[PDB]
């Protein structure tokens, strides 16, 4: 009876790009189809004076046949009418790395502790998501405090994803 239509999902009110800048460690991920980033995922967000948000990311990706590389990725965000909803053009510093353009929603954050991100790459015909991914980020690479963890769990459930995350390990691979 809970609403899993993407159009129903709340996102961060009055999202502040500047406050969101800096280092975010991925603690957990819900994978899309054909998953790319595997683990050791760290993102760096910036805003320029134009107010244009961008990011870089490092992580282990596993090219099939069991070949691990540390991907170095770049993203730039185009604003929409909602301050928390963006279009993210992304690519790798190496041209053979995955590129594309995904929706990028900041579902919730308190800026200095946790963030929940969401992307629906493809809708179902009933408005639910056919192919989604989601990152939970922490400022502290050692994880979230309990109050933040509990808030995040609520947000995960609201996205209809709470059963579908896996933990992201950080072990200096990159
Ligand atoms: C959304 C993660 C951080 C945002 C920083 C954008 C920098 C490019 C990251 C590329 C994400 C594309 C792969 C995401 C889906 C996946 O890993 O399976
Ligand atoms: Cl709990
Ligand atoms: Cl669960």
Image (tube, rainbow, N blue to C red):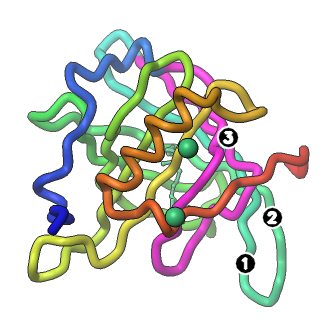
Q: Quadrant of the N terminus?
A: bottom left
Q: Characterize the magenta stretch by its predominant secondary structure.
A: strand
**Which percent across, then down, holds residue 151?**
44, 35
Does 118 appear above or below 77? below
Q: Nearer the viewer, residue 122 or 73?
A: 122
How far apart are labels 1 and 3 at the CA level? 19 Å
**Which percent across, then down, holds residue 12?**
27, 30
Q: Nearer the viewer, residue 10 or 119?
A: 10
**In the image, is 14 to the left or to the right of 74?**
left
- The quarter of the picture where residue 105 lies is top left
Q: Tag 2, which secondary structure?
A: strand
Kindly identify which numbered label has been placed on residue 69: 2
**What residue appears at the point 64 percent right and 32 percent down from the top-left corner?**
144
**In the image, is 163 to the left or to the right of 41?**
left
- Asked if the residue at tag 3 contacts the one at tag 1, i.e. Cβ–Cβ closer than 8 Å, the answer is no
Q: Would you say residue 1 sits in the magenta stretch? A: no
Region in magenta = 21-47
Identity of the residue furthest to the right in this view: 172
**In the image, is 100 to the left or to the right of 122?**
right
**Which percent across, then down, holds residue 174?**
85, 48
Mark toward the start of the polypeptide (1 vs 3): 3
Kindly identify which numbered label has been placed on residue 63: 1
Q: Which residue is mark 3?
A: 42
How far apart are labels 2 and 1 at the CA level? 7 Å
- Asked if the residue at tag 1 contacts the one at tag 2, i.e. Cβ–Cβ closer than 8 Å, the answer is yes
**In the image, is 52 to the left or to the right of 169?**
left
Does 166 appear above or below 25? below
């Amino acid at each position: 009876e809970r609403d899993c239509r993407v159009s129903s999902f709340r996102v961060k009110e009055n999202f502040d790009k500047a406050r969101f800048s800096g280092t975010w460690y991925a603690m957990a991920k819900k994978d899309p189809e054909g998953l790319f980033l595997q683990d050791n995922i760290v993102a760096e967000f910036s805003v320029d004076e134009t107010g244009q948000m961008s990011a870089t990311a490092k992580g282990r990706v596993r090219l099939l046949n069991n070949w691990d590389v540390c991907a170095d990725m770049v993203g730039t965000f185009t604003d929409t009418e909602d301050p928390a909803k963006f279009k993210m053009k992304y690519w790798g510093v190496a041209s053979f790395l995955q590129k594309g353009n995904d929706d990028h929603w900041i579902v919730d954050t308190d800026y200095d502790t946790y963030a929940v991100q969401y992307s629906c790459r493809l809708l179902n015909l009933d408005g639910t998501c056919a192919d989604s991914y989601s990152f939970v980020f922490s400022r502290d690479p050692n994880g979230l405090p309990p109050e933040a963890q509990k808030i995040v769990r609520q947000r995960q459930e609201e996205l209809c994803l709470a059963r579908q995350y896996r933990l992201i390990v950080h072990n200096g691979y990159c």
